[PDB]
Structures are given as structure tokens and as C-alpha cells.
Length: 50
Length: 51
Image (cartoon, rainbow over all chains, first blue to last red; front, side, top):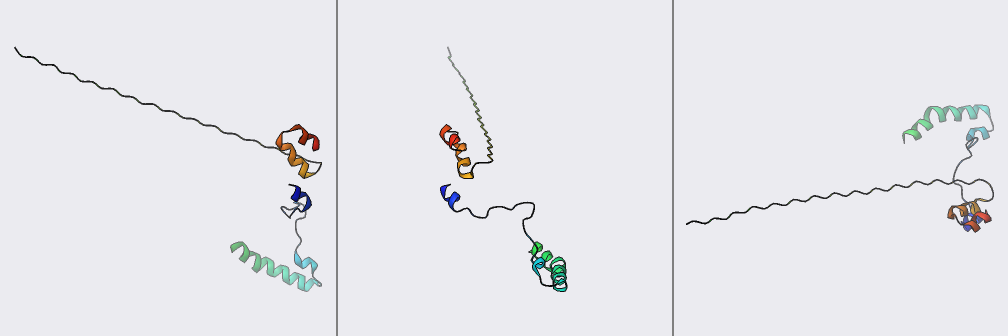
């Protein structure tokens, strides 16, 4: 417990804003939409299946 | 003149015992610091005071 006070590790999310989509960080709406569209249509289905 | 003796004996015993114990405990603490907060789960006053 003393070590946890000195060196806590990531254990859980803040449930209000846990993570942000990476294409929010994109330079450009065309790229960002392409990433979102591919994420929605292809990658997230595959990973949820995987 | 004839003699006969006959005996039959039977005994039966059955015994059944059952025991069951179940415990549940839930503790939660907010505020202070979490490391001292874990201390109150000892139930020991000095650790409660330390929290």
C-alpha cells in the first residue's frame, strides 16, 4: 500500500471522458472522415469479432 | 424330547449432519488519501484515526 501511494498504476477509466478517437487529432476532415468511415465500417467490426 | 432355540436380531442406524456458513462484507471509503483509507479496513482505531 505504501508503494501504491508512491507508484500507482493505471487501473480504471474516468467514465465521463475515458478516451478520444485518434482521428480527432487528424490534420484534415477528408482524412479524418476516411479514418472514421473505415473504423466504423471495417476495423471495429473486425476487432469486436476478433 | 426335542429342543430348539432360534433368535434373530437386527439393528439399523443412520445419522446425517449438515453445516453451512456464509459471510459477506463490503466496505468503502472516500476522501483523505487512499493508502490511509485502506487502513480503516483493519477496524483498528489508530488506523481509523490515521485516516
